[PDB]
Amino acid sequence: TAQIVAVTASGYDSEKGHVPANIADGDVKTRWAASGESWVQLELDKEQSIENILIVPFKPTERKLKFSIFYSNDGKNWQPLAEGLETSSADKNGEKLTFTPVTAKYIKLDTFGTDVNNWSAINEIAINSAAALPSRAIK
Ligand SMILES: [Ca+2]
């Protein structure tokens, strides 16, 4: 996987400490969570080729997360990989999202809550994962 060196976000659940770094700590038991329309931004160690994103949303069989994914080299000007996606509720395995490869230093997810409530909660994200999951092409 591509090294995530820094994570930032619009906000987070500070009472439970569901901080942005939890999205990239390699532990599916910790999560980032924020309410309302939110965003979480992943900075890689360098600009590099991106071919997949692994997303492990919280309570996936109960809650489908609505989100969009953007990429950038400067962290200021964004291009979409896909907009208005929902995560699957089929199982608890996460999903491997695929797309025409791009070059990026930053990946940003703009999130819109779930079909259950207005929290966005993600256990883990990884970039260029080898997870043994079927490819879900997103655009
Ligand atoms: Ca985590």
Image: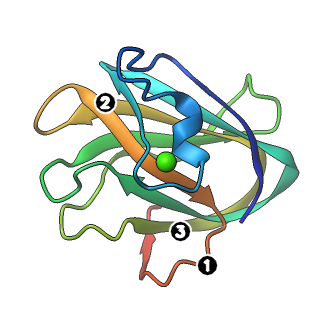
Give residue 112's mark: 2
Looking at the image, tell me whether mark 3 or mark 2 is earlier in sequence order. 3
Q: Percent position (x, y) of residue 2?
A: 75, 59
The residue at the point 87 percent across, 49 percent down is 47
Discs 3, 1 touching: Cβ within 8 Å: no
Q: CA distance from mark 3 to mark 1?
A: 12 Å
Q: Percent position (x, y) of residue 121?
A: 34, 38
State left or right for residue 19 relative to residue 84: right
Under mark 3, the amino acid is Thr
The residue at the point 61 percent across, 70 percent down is 129
Q: CA distance from mark 2 to mark 1?
A: 27 Å
Under mark 1, the amino acid is Ala
In the rendered image, the vertical position of residue 93 relative to residue 36, given as above or below: below
Looking at the image, tell me whether mark 3 or mark 1 is earlier in sequence order. 3
State left or right for residue 113 relative to residue 61: right
In the rendered image, the vertical position of residue 55 relative to residue 76, given as above or below: below
In the rendered image, the vertical position of residue 74 relative to residue 64, given as above or below: above
Q: Secondary structure at mark 2?
A: strand
Mark 2, mark 1: which one is toward the viewer?
1
Under mark 2, the amino acid is Phe
Q: Nearer the viewer, residue 43 or 77?
A: 43
The residue at the point 82 percent across, 30 percent down is 74
Q: Percent position (x, y) of residue 43?
A: 74, 38
In the rendered image, which quarter is residue 107 located in? top right
Q: Secondary structure at mark 3?
A: strand
Q: Nearer the viewer, residue 88 or 81?
A: 88
Give residue 23's mark: none
Residue holding disc 1? 130
Q: Secondary structure at mark 1?
A: loop
Residue holding disc 3? 98
State left or right for residue 3 relative to residue 70: right
Classify 10 Å Cα crowding around label 2: few (below 14), some (14-19), many (20 and above): many
